[PDB]
Picture 1: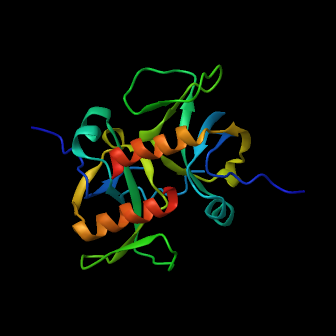
Picture 2: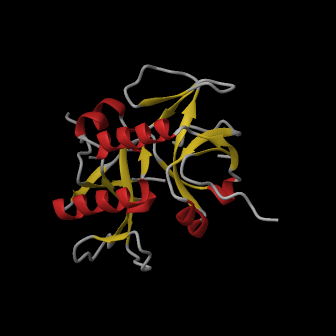
Picture 3: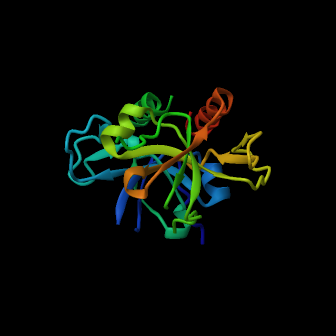
Length: 100
Length: 107
């Protein structure tokens, strides 16, 4: 009965079929059916803003410059896992390097 | 002749689930010139003249249209492909506040 609501640090899965890491807080996400997230991939091309997600067999890197707003409820999202507070603080760090 | 490259603070206009379309549409550029130039991508947040009193809105004032930048709406977009053009820039105030709210969300 209860629908999954993306939380900050969650690695979710979407359509649109691509992994992402949610930087938006649970309440924002729930009220707005949207979240801020960054896309992840099985391919690390060494671009500087790439943030390695630990020892990944699947979903190897997270792109912090690719930040964006998506409607998680609309396209649906499920939980592929969560992200080490390290990786989260870091990613926010990079993003700040760019946006700050 | 050199193409316009969007700079941090610039208000641009884009060709541009993916609700927002507004085939000719405003955005505020959060990425610095270098990055935008190299990547053909930039980070920006969408603008509209309609204020919903929504908590993440930032007022952009004084111009042809008084409006709001929607600061929870940050987007990585490809401006070269989408044909971004310069609509002028935002006061240091407004940009700073945008950054701030974004921090609210992700901080």
